[PDB]
């Protein structure tokens, strides 16, 4: 048989993020230790301004 | 580019005979964000997949 | 002689820090990116490397 085929080929460059999956953002927290996800460069820390 | 996508809509579709992935696991896509998507599309023989 | 002993230790620490950033054949050197991109059955192979 014939088959329809698709390839999705994400680019993980060190560059401005431009397509996301849906996860809802939340308020910024200062001087508290928190788990953080900016644009998928996830980590844990004290977000100081 | 410059949009949001719910990959779980694709994941939950039983219509796909394979959903194979090589550098991300297909549950985690909804939590990720990317620089380019690059979707490629074609028709081939089922034996060629 | 004293400057030499300080420099050799500072080089050892700079080396040991840079080695964190090396792939060693895994898909990333940022450990948290692996843990966010992959499920354990796949991630255990990368993290073992």
Image (cartoon, rainbow, N blue to C red):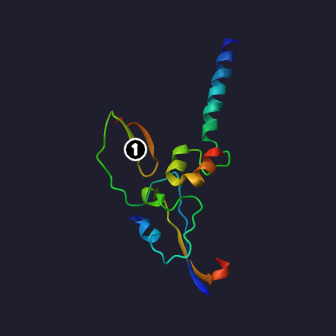
Q: Residue furthest right?
A: C1
| Horizontal arrangement in the rendering, residue A27 relative to residue C27 (left or right) | left
Label 1: chain? A
Note whether B43 is above or below A40 in the view shown.
below
Q: Residue furthest bottom?
A: A1
Question: Quadrant where the C terminus of chain C lies?
Answer: top right
Q: Residue at x 43, y 39 (%)?
A: A44
Whole-percent x and y of residue A26? 30, 49
| Horizontal arrangement in the rendering, residue B36 relative to residue A45 (left or right) | right
Q: Quadrant of residue A31?
A: top left
Q: Residue at x 33, y 52 (%)?
A: A25
Whole-percent x and y of residue C24? 67, 45
Note whether A23 is above or below B11 in the view shown.
above
Disc 1 is placed on an element classified as strand
Total of numbered circles in the picture?
A: 1
Whole-percent x and y of residue C32? 51, 45
Q: Quadrant of residue A21?
A: bottom left
Q: Residue furthest top?
A: C2
| Horizontal arrangement in the rendering, residue A32 relative to residue A18 (left or right) | left
Whole-percent x and y of residue B15? 49, 78
Judge whether residue C7 can be spotted in this image. yes
Q: Residue at x 58, y 83 (%)?
A: A3
Q: Quadrant of residue C9?
A: top right
Q: Residue furthest left?
A: A27
Graded by Cα atoms within 10 Å as few (under 14), some (14 to 19) or many (20 or more), the crowding at tag 1 reads some
- Towards the viewer: B10 or B12: B12
Judge whether residue C23 can be spotted in this image. no
- Towards the viewer: A39 or B26: B26
- Towards the viewer: C40 or B20: C40
Question: Quadrant where the N terminus of chain C lies?
Answer: top right
Residue hosting label 1: A36
């Amino acid at each position: 048989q014939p088959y329809r085929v698709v390839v999705l080929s994400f680019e993980l460059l060190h560059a401005p993020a431009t397509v996301c999956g849906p996860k809802k953002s939340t308020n910024l927290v200062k001087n508290k230790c928190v788990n953080f996800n900016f644009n998928g460069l996830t980590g844990t820390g004290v977000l100081t301004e | 580019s410059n949009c949001v996508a719910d990959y779980s809509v694709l994941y939950n579709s039983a219509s796909f005979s394979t959903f194979k992935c090589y550098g991300v696991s297909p549950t985690k896509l909804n939590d990720l964000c990317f620089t380019n998507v690059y979707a490629d599309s074609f028709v081939i023989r089922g034996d060629e997949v | 002689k004293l400057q030499d002993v300080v420099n050799q230790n500072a080089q050892a620490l700079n080396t040991l820090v840079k080695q964190l950033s090396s792939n060693f054949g895994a898909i990333s050197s940022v450990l948290n990116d692996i843990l966010s991109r992959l499920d354990p059955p796949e991630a255990e192979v990368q993290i073992d490397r």
